[PDB]
Length: 85
Ligand SMILES: [Ca+2]
Image (cartoon, rainbow, N blue to C red; front, side, top):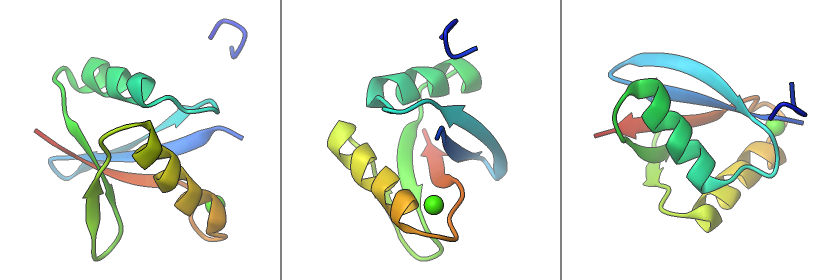
């Protein structure tokens, strides 16, 4: 935190607006959830999205698998997350 002052860049989309927020590894599900609530001023569900599919991320295991997609892809530079109330 203060020490922090390989990150995972998450591109959040909420109501058509996008922004990128970086998270240090290992990325904790509870930390992403907290950052979303803090930044957007309300809790929002995390949906990993590609051009065709989205999947709700329910827990650390789901988040780890989504980050692994990111890490296995040479072209993907951020993790696309659709936020829904
Ligand atoms: Ca990558």
